[PDB]
Image (tube, coloured by chain):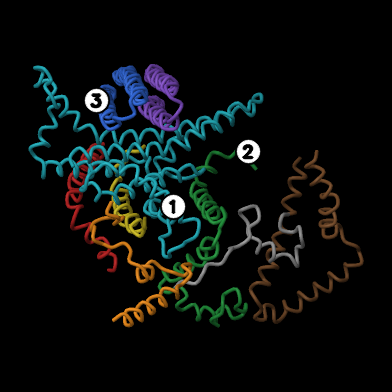
Chain colours: A green, C cyan, D orange, E red, F yellow, G brown, H purple, I blue
Amino acid sequence: KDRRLLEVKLGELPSWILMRDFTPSGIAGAFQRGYYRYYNKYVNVKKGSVAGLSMVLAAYVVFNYCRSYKELKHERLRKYH
Amino acid sequence: PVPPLPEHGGKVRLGLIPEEFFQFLYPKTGVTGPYV
Amino acid sequence: NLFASFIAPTMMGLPIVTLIIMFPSLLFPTPKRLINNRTISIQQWLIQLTSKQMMAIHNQKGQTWSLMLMSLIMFIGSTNILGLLPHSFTPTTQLSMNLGMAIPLWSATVFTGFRYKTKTSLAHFLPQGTPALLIPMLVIIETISLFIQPVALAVRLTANITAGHLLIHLIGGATLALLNINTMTAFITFTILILLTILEFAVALIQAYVFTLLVSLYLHD
Amino acid sequence: LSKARIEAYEKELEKMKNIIPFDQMTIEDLNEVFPETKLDKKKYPYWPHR
Amino acid sequence: QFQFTGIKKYFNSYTLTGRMNCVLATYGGIALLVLYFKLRSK
Amino acid sequence: QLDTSTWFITITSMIMTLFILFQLKISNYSY
Amino acid sequence: VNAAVTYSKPRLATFWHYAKVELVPPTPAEIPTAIQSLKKIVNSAQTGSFKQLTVKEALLNGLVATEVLMWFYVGEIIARA
Amino acid sequence: IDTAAKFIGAGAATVGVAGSGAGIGTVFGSLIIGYARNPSLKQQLFSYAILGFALSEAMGLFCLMVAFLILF
Amino acid sequence: IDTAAKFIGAGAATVGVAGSGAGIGTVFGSLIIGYARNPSLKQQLFSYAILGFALSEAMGLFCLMVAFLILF
């Protein structure tokens, strides 16, 4: 049904696909929800910690590593097999 | 008239991994499961 | 090899230089309440502290430029610091945007000076006071000195960051090679020592870049 | 006249006594309660009279 | 939409002089044309 | 390496971000 | 030394009881229990299967399966020397 | 043919660091004498010294970039 | 060979930029000691310093421009 995807039944996945309407909310709506879900939970408190930014920085680092794989494995490989 | 903010957010182990992942695998993996 | 990160405008099926350059803005939440959390109070305190130290010279017209200068300094400073990450791509490395930054503001200042104070703006070429009888010689000196400002203002930024990254990469390669032959932690010590200077060398460049433009604007205002 | 002025002052004091604890306050409501900054110094990012 | 009115005063008031990006555009176009000619020469 | 004559996109994106995003967020400040 | 007292002694007392209970070769008496669990798997495999269950349970099963996958990788390193 | 010329050109170009060394030596040397004038304001003079050293380093660092350019 | 000559000439041309570092170091070194003597005239001192730094950069960039022109 309209419940969260982590709560929908396994056999109800095609049913929830029909319920996926308005979940993107023109794509941008889902991003609008997702930004505030994290921001209002780990940042917008009376007193936060360094954990607010470290997740984003680590995600940025891993995303950057994903791009350059082509060149690295191209020749930087040490051994064979 | 914005309501007051909560005093705390969430608890994170090692400063990078939240506690919810540890709680999720606790019944099956155990206390020391996910580190392995 | 070495010149791989620089000549790599965010390699992908579709270029994503826009995404890379617009990312830093997602770190400055806008205030929405009288009393806010800790992460934005420090930001606004820093902005207040920096504002009162630089824009406290211009009389009335230069106070209008305050927002532009603060935005510029924050943008360049945020772009430079984010580049220290292991596999980042600093947009300030490219000469294109450095050339697209200097010319507009310099032109704005130079033909703002002529519009309102043409008599005095024309006089600044000749140095104040009597310079003996060498007038024609120095008249051609300061006018050619005028045109070099944007070129240097862009080239120093384009050069220093690349030099720093080259040094870091070469020292890393050196400390990797010497693992096989003998044992020397002096190289990693050099790396960790140099990293402090490279970390604190960006903000000085931001400050110098902004301050030179502040001085240039104040001359014709 | 004095009694009218006294009643007005009593009303104003009652208004002043009832006040939000400033944690839920926004910037506009503080302008409502007390006079504060304005937008007379146009084309400014601070509007402080410098 | 609802963002033009936010900084409309700035745009029509003080950035009139700074709005002269024509020099940069002409320089970039000339440089690109020269580079294209050199590449076509081969 | 830095001169490959593909300078249009970077200039356009820098102008957009600098002259829209940062000024609008920085305007909503008090002192 | 003192850090060894505060960790390795808890490694041999706290971590020892944490792990040795859950990390030890099993008694042969549980083999019929595992076979009965295999029968549990088969019953759903023939019919029912997902039976419109929660996604979270499937995620738990997959995560434990991946943990099991890792040991085979460890064995290759052991044999490589 | 060209390898030797490029290598010797790089080796000759790398001698531009002397000016920066002399400049940074001069600035820090002036700072200690200036501080000794009055122990107050030490942070201000220190800020001036740091600015001067950074400026000299920027003015002298782009010499090695030409060497790396000729090398590759 | 002619290209090799251009490369070696460009490499040897850049060595003249070392003068900028020494001049920059000297001008800034004077500002700190002078300010320390008379902490009243900050504005004129800084204006003169900026003028000196602007004028002193011309020669080194001129030599670098000559090297760039001769190489290409």
Q: Quadrant of the C terminus of chain A?
A: top right
Give the residue number, with chain letter if any, for mark 2: A79
Give the residue number, with chain letter if any, for mark 1: C43
Give the residue number, with chain letter if any, for mark 3: I55
Residue I48: where, in percent of width, then height?
Answer: 26, 27
Residue type marked 3: Leu
Tell me the residue at 75%/67% (across/down): B27
Residue in front for this viewpoint, H37 or A75: H37
* Discs 2 and 3 share one subunit: no
**Mark 3 neighbour density, 10 Å: few (under 14) some (14–19) many (20 or more):** few
CA separation in Å, label 3 and label 1: 37 Å
**Secondary structure beneath label 3:** helix
Label tally: 3
Residue H43: where, in percent of width, then height?
Answer: 44, 32
**Mark 2 neighbour density, 10 Å: few (under 14) some (14–19) many (20 or more):** few
Residue type marked 2: Lys
Q: Check if mark 2's residue and mark 3's residue have beta carbons within 8 Å.
A: no
Q: Check if mark 3's residue and mark 1's residue have beta carbons within 8 Å.
A: no
